[PDB]
Length: 99
Length: 99
Image (cartoon, rainbow over all chains, first blue to last red; front, side, top):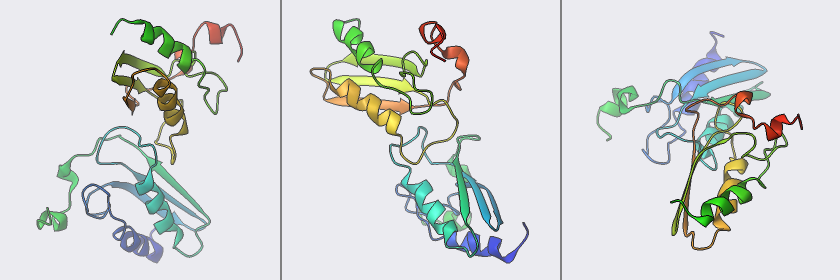
């Protein structure tokens, strides 16, 4: 799955922003795994707080972002708390202080 | 919080059915904790499968069920995977074989 769509996928996700922290899911370190292999795309991610929300809007935005990739007919977005997220996963870039 | 609303709460939840297993959340062993103390109600529950769903419809139905209790102005429904659910949590009643 080492292809140009992978790089494109990362760019797309960098445009998906978290509701609470105001930063994109990539710099926030919410993306645990990403695999793009047409016709499928898989992403394992987490949320910044424990518990499943009534509407996983962030997960939906991530799915829709990956769907923008050509040839991706199926997107599997798995939201997990293993391991549990903490601010230590923030990027240096997001540590270049927007916070 | 040892009151008659607690018993009423259990009856209400026994009327909320899981989408996949076709059994109510109580007999399925999905309710981990329940505290009813007007004006508040708290419930910690889990789901039969890992991962946070796009729409936690079951959690919503549980919340709405508890809202039927008189004097409950705030309902906190926490969906957790700690500990992780398994069929071993099924009730004898639900083990009186509906499955």
